[PDB]
Image (cartoon, rainbow, N blue to C red):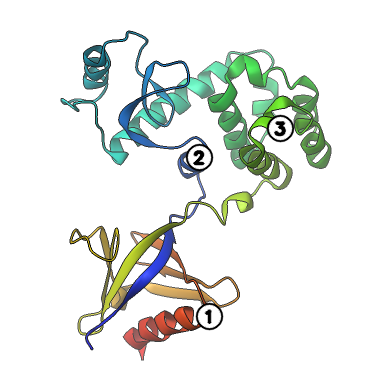
Amino acid sequence: GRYLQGYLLKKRRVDNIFEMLRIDEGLRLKIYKNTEGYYTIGIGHLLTKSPSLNAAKSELDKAIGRNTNGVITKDEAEKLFNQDVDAAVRGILRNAKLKPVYDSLDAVRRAALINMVFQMGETGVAGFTNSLRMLQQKRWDEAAVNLAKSRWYNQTPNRAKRVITTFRTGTWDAYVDQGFKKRFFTLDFRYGTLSYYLNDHNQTCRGEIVISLSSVSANKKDKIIIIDSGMEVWVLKATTKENWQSWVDALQTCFD
């Protein structure tokens, strides 16, 4: 018995605007027609409006320094994301209604505002005048109840509640239970390397951490196990207490 193996849920810690919008908006790698039928990609990145897939592929090809072919990488989507964030921030700072509030907010709540911009557009966010005033005055709890008095809150409830919670607390707590995906893990007892795969079968190794060089933190109540390699952090979640204990004991062997 050289390998401890089995399924576990995995996610990346949501503690920055990219991971947040990745959860809330979504990150697509293949060119997809957005809601208005215009070729889009990554995290709400508008390519153009021409019904020519070749045009979009080229505007996308001019976007990234290569011939994507209607498909991009996650690292690429991020690059388009960072550009869109800068455009969003500048738009906000040039909008007389949003600048004041944005100047008064902290980094985390600022990401929450941008999140709203991505979803409903700058002018749409400027329509929450009463909530904006409250956030500017730092009346967190009151801003939260008002932000909820809107179509947004009723149409996209879950996303809305997460953004509002972020405005209320100034923390990333609304996203702790978000971003989990089922993956198959393999721990090699002989050399101490932990690898994961898309599933039971597939051969392609999607990631790997040398346990003996990482920090392993675990929480039984949440059935969470956090593995920090220094340059990468995996947040894993077991399906039961037995399953959870089996992995924690196995990873603990790398330190006795």
Q: Find the residue positioned furthest to the bottom.
A: 256
Give the label on residue 11, or none: none
Circle 3 residues within 10 Å: few <14, some 14–19, many ≥20: few
The residue that disc 2 covers is 17
Give coordinates of residue 224: x percent, y percent: 51, 70
- The answer to whether the residues at label 2 and label 3 have Cβ atoms under 8 Å apart is no
| Closest to the observer, 181 or 15 | 181
Eyeballing the image, is 168 above or below 56?
A: below
Disc 3 on helix, strand or loop?
Answer: helix
Q: Quadrant of residue 94?
A: top right
The residue that disc 3 covers is 154
Q: Residue at the spot x=36%, y=84% of the render?
A: 250
The residue that disc 1 covers is 241
Q: Quadrant of residue 186?
A: bottom left
Dot 1 or dot 2, earlier in sequence: 2
Eyeballing the image, is 233 above or below 48?
A: below
Q: Residue at the spot x=32%, y=84% of the render?
A: 254
Task: Tell me the quarter of the image containing the C terminus.
Answer: bottom left
| Closest to the observer, 69 or 33 | 33
Q: Left or right: where does residue 183 sit relative to residue 19?
A: left
- How far is the residue under mark 2 from the one under mark 3? 23 Å
Dot 3 or dot 1, earlier in sequence: 3
Disc 2 on helix, strand or loop?
Answer: helix
Dot 2 or dot 3, earlier in sequence: 2
